Amino acid sequence: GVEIETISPGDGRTFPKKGQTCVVHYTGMLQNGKKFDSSRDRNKPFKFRIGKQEVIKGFEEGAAQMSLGQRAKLTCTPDVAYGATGHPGVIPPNATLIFDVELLNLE
Image 1 (cartoon, rainbow, N blue to C red):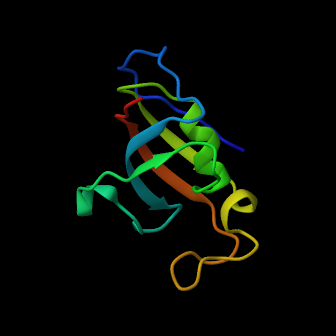
Image 2: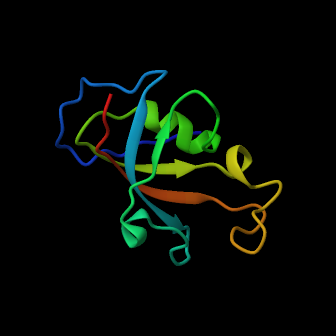
């Protein structure tokens, strides 16, 4: 389940496609919890592509449902990313994830 609550401005037409390398200022957030991840800290804004399942599934569908300049807010279910397993020491099992995502990409 992917839920989008878009902070408005951007273009709304340039959509991410396959074979496209994209740049995301992501920010991790725990539901009823503190932060766990931020691309704003390292300031190297995480160049990655679409179509190799490099990212988790909840972040994957949220990438395609955005456009250039936009600023969405993800809501990831536990079963698509880590809710069965839990990432060791960082993300507990059965965890619901919140993301602050801005798409300022190329291609």
